[PDB]
Image 1 (tube, rainbow over the protein chains, first blue to last red):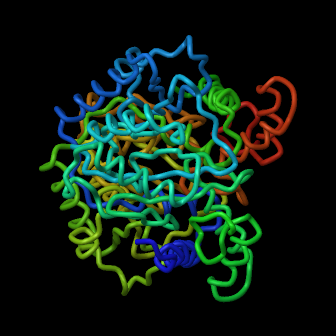
Image 2: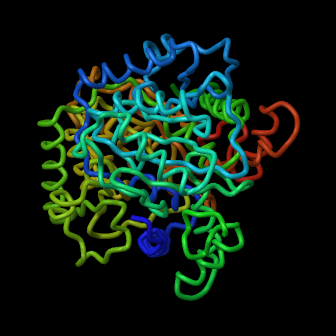
Image 3: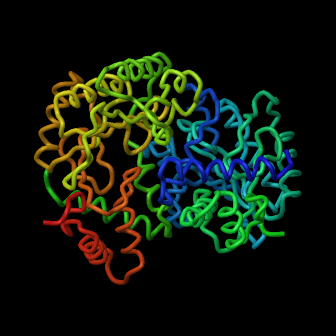
Length: 255
Length: 255
């Protein structure tokens, strides 16, 4: 797991694929990363219904708020998850933020941990993420995708963590334990350019000031490199250096 | 249907949503358009298998090739749709291109017609699209999404057409008739900034030299508008005009 070889290799494969496909826009490059589909079995009607029941429950807690990303414009007073899940069918597909009632600010040294489980275990993992968030203040936020798309694109469950690679390895294994999810419940998949840290666990450090929404930071590195001449590897290493990443590991901040 | 009012209005709602959410990147603005979900019922497992079977069958037509977008880097003699469907999980989720054997180039006057049906009619629609392409050279290409994501984002089935609004309105009605899908099987849904041309039918024109992959052209107008000052409506119209669109109707080319 913890070697930079595959991490850089997948990043190069992503960038070479974009050049070979003829993609030359941010959206076009990003979709290669995003639509990279893991082998999963979707939730049935019952499971999807149960998944949304779980989210509503977490929202009715005193310390945790569950809000769709499409509601980022709303004051906390205007949030209505019940009305959302009942009326807005983006509830089946969009991402929901899991946000602790104490806010917890991202500091300069933060990253994202992506967790892949079979969709039937999605509700269970969500509960575990909430539990991990109660005790560990280093975990600032979580995100889970709607049930209809759970397991059908490169990520479905993400934690934002203040800290470094070491902290994320520790927290990932602690999450696995807390979850009670069997080893067969976790999905072997590493999104392109992310550091695999374990079965179903993947990590990337953020660099302050780089575009971060929807996980798009590494797209911009590739965009720079696409303007260049030569074997892809060098163009990537220099683009990584210029934007503050480790040139030998695109998942990490420079030293 | 054929009024500019709604078309400009949904475009302005998109841009206002982007500003309210604080989205300020191409991907972040694009996702508001893309993740806008219509109310549909997903395919069951038999229906998904049938759908993939239909696709594989269509590729056996002598004047038609079905190729996934992720194979844009392949020469025709490198394609293997059968192997892709059996072995690549992207086949469940990715877009498939429907491409004529004798290449019809997209012209300066070209647009997209987006067609929305309940996922259980998706296979029937694909058959209808392929047949439309046998008869009409004006239709240069078609795209349909993998079965697991059919009906789960703003678009699932698209035709590329050389011609204008009138041609699109006509081909759309023809396609609906041709398909034998019942009126009830079409989905009321217009992707943001597209011109509604009928129940389940939406259209937009491309401007020479604007970015079009993944349907992303109008995202760039919004990025322009978000950098400016004043009421959004005025900023959008200026941005529209500068990039070659009708200021009163964002789905149309100028003049």
